[PDB]
Structures are given as structure tokens and as C-alpha cells.
Amino acid sequence: GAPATVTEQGEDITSKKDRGVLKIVKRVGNGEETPMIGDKVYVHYKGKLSNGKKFDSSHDRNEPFVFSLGKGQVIKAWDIGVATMKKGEICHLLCKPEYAYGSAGSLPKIPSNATLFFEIELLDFKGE
Ligand SMILES: NC(=O)c1cccnc1
Ligand SMILES: NC(=O)c1cccnc1
Ligand SMILES: [Cl-]
Ligand code: NA
Ligand code: NA
Image 1 (cartoon, rainbow, N blue to C red):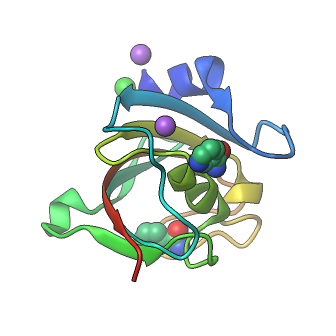
Image 2 (cartoon, protein in one colour):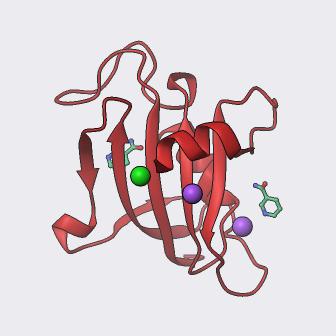
């Protein structure tokens, strides 16, 4: 399925080239521009654990998730992955725990040492 495919066929987007975040572009976005550090970014996403369970979805909330890019307000994989995206792009990200929640995990649903799968849509970005 999609998690296996990004695991086996994804592109390493890390600056360390440590395989910690792998990406596949699913829907090509618009233009060439990617967001700027500090921009307000608006995303829709769904996240799955490696046991197949969905642990989060903004679609199910009927509102996007908003954060300031490159500030550590989200897991490292999202700061580095969203920075690669164009407006309107949809990608898959396969994130090792060192770029996610590490040994701590995150209650209620994310265990220790978890590799995570996300589908992310970059809806918009704006400098404030
Ligand atoms: N910390 C995070 O990366 C995050 C992203 C979306 C929802 N909750 C947490
Ligand atoms: N974060 C990146 O890899 C990147 C590269 C070029 C332009 N925008 C983002
Ligand atoms: Cl799938
Ligand atoms: Na595929
Ligand atoms: Na891109």
C-alpha cells in the first residue's frame, strides 16, 4: 500500500541524507515557489501508524492545521517536508522516529519509537 511504497520508493529529503524522511509527490502543485521560513502554512493531512491505524486527520475536523514554518512548532519531518512543497501539492511522507516523536511518543495514540506515514496537502502559505 501507500506506506510501503513511500518506504521503498520515496526520496530522501533530509539534509543529512540519513533516510529519516522519505517523500513522494502525489499531486503536483502550482508554480515553483515553496514557502519561506516563518510563513504561516495551511495544511490538510492524515496520519497513520505502522500498524495501519489512523491517528489524526484535519479533514475529519473540517479545518486546516496552521503553523509557522521552520520554527519547531511541528515535528521535524513536517518542517523539512512542508518546506519542499508547492502550493496545491499533495505528498506522502514516511518519517522515522528521530524526525517525529522519538522515544517519548505522544499520547494518546503514538507509541515510543514510531515510524509515521502522512499524506499532506499544502493549501496555502503567507508571510505575516
Ligand atoms: N507536533 C506536530 O507535528 C503536530 C501536527 C499536527 C497535529 N498535532 C501535532
Ligand atoms: N527545503 C528544500 O529542500 C527546498 C529546496 C529548494 C526550494 N525550496 C525548498
Ligand atoms: Cl494504501
Ligand atoms: Na503507489
Ligand atoms: Na515540491
